[PDB]
Length: 84
Ligand SMILES: [Pr+3]
Ligand SMILES: [Pr+3]
Ligand SMILES: [Pr+3]
Image (cartoon, rainbow, N blue to C red; front, side, top):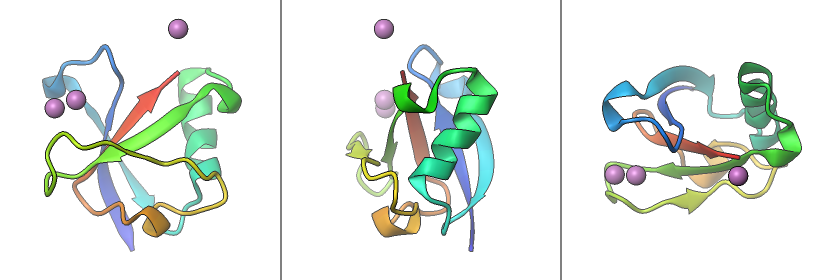
């Protein structure tokens, strides 16, 4: 299953968020790898969380690099929040 996710950085307006299509089976390590190469920020520095429109405003940390997006129940249309 492919997830279409919004990608938000802290300084961005909600109106200017990016999107990416990612497999749900992708590990958090590999999502950080992708973001690291895009942003030129080290993998070790990235902090990822997500939010669902089902529970507006609640952030869930994507903490365990070995686990997948699916493990955390990230769904189509959710928003990945990226900090460093
Ligand atoms: Pr908000
Ligand atoms: Pr927010
Ligand atoms: Pr700082």
